[PDB]
Length: 164
Ligand SMILES: [Cl-]
Ligand SMILES: [Cl-]
Ligand SMILES: [K+]
Image 1 (cartoon, rainbow, N blue to C red):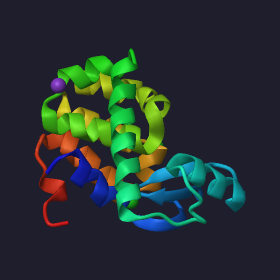
Image 2: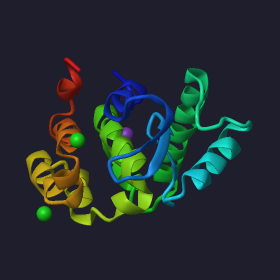
Image 3: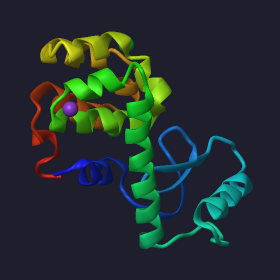
């Protein structure tokens, strides 16, 4: 189990434009295309991202390419972030995956706003952080995914992804 498998489980894989849990146009493995309500806008963004006229659909290889770029961007974003970097450096490898997952889902900005939880993670107060993390819109909107991620932070194991 590694970050790619983890996210593949949480995001799934769709080769045609679809709407994510928030109603935004997305494709592949959770690759957000646009927050705009225009499907044409999304189709444009798609073509631009892939480098060809896709007409709303892509191949598995294309999906995977986007996925690699996205994971790379999330990690890179974490490392450039003054509030995120220290936490990421302080965590073990498994727990670092949980942080990357959050950033992939909600962006650097979103995550950087979980100040209190971040501080608790930095201090390695696992149960305390887990409770704090659950007091959020994130947990209330996507509870199953949030539970998996929170369990990962709490335990430092892949148990929540075992049998999925
Ligand atoms: Cl709440
Ligand atoms: Cl969920
Ligand atoms: K680390």
